[PDB]
Length: 528
Ligand SMILES: Nc1nc2c(ncn2[C@@H]2O[C@H](COP(=O)(O)OP(=O)(O)O)[C@@H](O)[C@H]2O)c(=O)[nH]1
Ligand SMILES: [Mg+2]
Image 1 (cartoon, protein in one colour):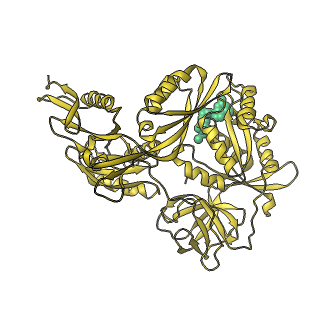
Image 2 (cartoon, protein in one colour):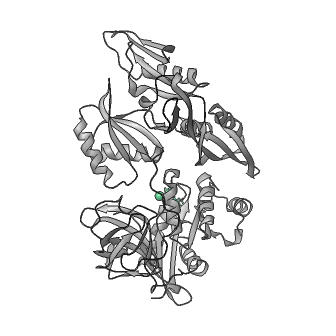
Image 3 (cartoon, helix red, strand yellow):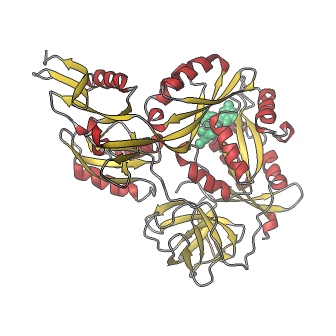
């Protein structure tokens, strides 16, 4: 059909508000490998039938880049808000990302069936915090198909149709991908200009690598191959591509022979932020761990890893993740998809270290590599992030105190309503990736939410602490901490480790040292 009858949208909501539930009602309503680039047909009330494309988006800050790329592939977005919850951290962050991509935003208040639902409140938040017309808000219940058709109409009537020329040089944005054992590395794309069909020879603009398309199509919801994809469409492309790192998200696919003038803007290679050592546990061996990682990696273009060994732990891997959730996902899937037993060290951020006789600043991804000789260090910088927090006013005080305990600098504070506070803090990421999520959760009864974004590196007074077990240091336990927090971390780690190690005939003396100086000791008496 015509592009004027096409609608490209996505759903963006704080986790738990009903994104998945709603995608089903939408598909179910219209109807009669992960879910992505879903094509639907909808006969509107105006009589015309429209071709709708549901682009699934990540929900965690760890996948922020990927989220932006998915938004760049749509013309609009459904901003799903839980009527019993109201606006939360991810709600605001995602809203602005959508705003930045110039998307028509359709707010939908979900769970209006719940006894705790308060649509009037949420409407007030939408207008005051988001600056949207509460009137545009679509009340709904994805749990009870209430408001589905109303959504589909808003999408047809509110979201503009794609604007592109199928006669112009191909220009397709890669917003997602996965590895198909049979089709190879598969790219989920948005076609801006031109058309693409099996047999065509494409080219990846960031690499200049060329391939020959083997198949094109979309999920309906099953992976259906079409004979082509044209400007405005959303689907997938296969072309005998070795792996997902060849079709990086945010990249542009054009024709090898007649390439488009410029690629879609905003391309960025994956950037690991948090690292950790993963070591084989129980009976699992190194090989089984290595083999499992190689297999998992095939379906994950962001993860990086390299062989690492420690005195006590033996051989493992130093793995880099996009964040904490990404690490968790990898952990669970490694033990659940390949059933390997692993112990994971405390995570760490990448530090920039300038040492006296080395011209170039060194990037430290493994604490073990942080210079032991503190005298040789000219300076060290660490990544900082801007943290946004939304909480009921009753907990603002405890949260504020938690944030400053963790070296946070308050930059702003506002009320989203008479009982809801909004906060912004600049914090070292190293402080955020250690017990911040739970602390913030327990003190707010799980009511406070937060989000954050990298704002760059800043020099800080950090130092390396080493752990000694019976006068013998285990490098895998050394860590970097701010000089002012050292004593506390030392105590925490010492007291934590004692209860982390079982008894034995010999007394186990645990020591946390600072450059040869023990600043925390803990001992677990012999085996009874
Ligand atoms: N009562 C009620 N529950 C809902 C509604 N929408 C979603 N839920 C439930 O909220 C929980 C999480 O839903 P989900 O779609 O996975 O949220 P996501 O985290 O945004 O995907 C599940 O129990 C859903 O069934 C709704 O409109 N009303
Ligand atoms: Mg979901």
